[PDB]
Every structure is written in structure tokens, then in C-alpha cells.
Image (cartoon, rainbow, N blue to C red; front, side, top):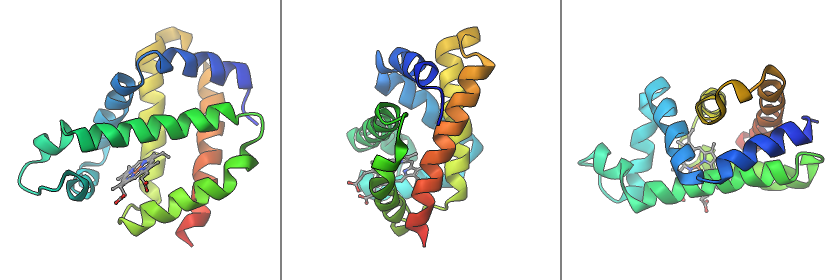
Length: 147
Ligand code: HEM
């Protein structure tokens, strides 16, 4: 159970510009794991240009979906069991498109980077710990989807 106010007050800041913050998360994620980008080519409907896929409405829509999912976790920070079935279904969908479960740990590192970029020293160790616990719960629920 992550401290709710630390999660809510930090998420509120990133919610002011969710697409811009999501782009920052993905930029770190791709630098840490370059193999992830070719998975998005199918949604883009073209395999010739990674850069065109990165700037595509289809890629932006995925960023919007990711921010909505994190928003649902933040809304349910007090009880994440409500989203257990949905997160397992999300885990199934990612396994279906070739995503490895290990890449979700890399997404967690990118999320902390996005938050530190947005908040600076306001991203306190307690805030970082709260986000680590919340994200760890989200990936533990999504992990059951892989089975
Ligand atoms: C590891 C990086 C990620 C990759 C490679 C990835 C890949 C994908 C792909 C390829 C799709 C499209 C599936 C399809 O319809 O064919 C998708 C859908 C989706 N992704 Fe991700 N994703 C990643 C991270 C995340 C994260 C961290 C979340 C939030 C937990 C998320 C939330 C979603 C959602 C909500 C959809 C909904 C599409 C649907 O209706 O099924 N993604 N993902």
C-alpha cells in the first residue's frame, strides 16, 4: 500500500501535461531497451521508418493509453486489488504481442526518471519509494497474465 498523498500529489503534477511526460518516459525506455521499438511498428502499419513510427498518432495513442493505466493505479492506490483482473488482461495482451515481462522493470526505471525530470528535488526519497511500491504492485498483477 503506497502512501496515497505522495502518489496523488506527484501524479497531479504529471497529469497537467500527460503526453509530454509520457514521451519523456518512452525516450528513456528506448535508450535502455532499443529492441522494444520494433514491436510498435505493427501498430504504425509501416516497417521502413522507426522515426516516423515514433512521431505517429498510433505511437501517441499508446502513450495516452499508458498514462490512463497509471492514472487508474493512482485512483486505486488505496486498494489495487480492484484492478487485479484488468492488469492480468493487460499482461496477457503484452505477452501476446511479444513483450517480455523483464521490459516492465525497465518501464519502472523510466517512470522514476520521468517523475524526477518533472519534479526535481520535490521527488523526495519517500515519493520515490511510494512510486516503486505502486509500480511493483502493478507489474506483479500484470505478471499473472504471462502464465
Ligand atoms: C515495455 C514497453 C511496452 C511495449 C513494448 C508495449 C507494446 C504494446 C503494443 C504493441 C500494444 C498494442 C497491442 C495491439 O493492439 O496489437 C500495446 C497496447 C497497450 N499497452 Fe502497451 N507496451 C508497453 C508498455 C506499456 C505499459 C507500461 C502500459 C501500462 C501498464 C501499457 C498499456 C497498454 C494498453 C492499455 C494497451 C491497450 C491496447 C488494447 O486495446 O489492447 N503499455 N502495448
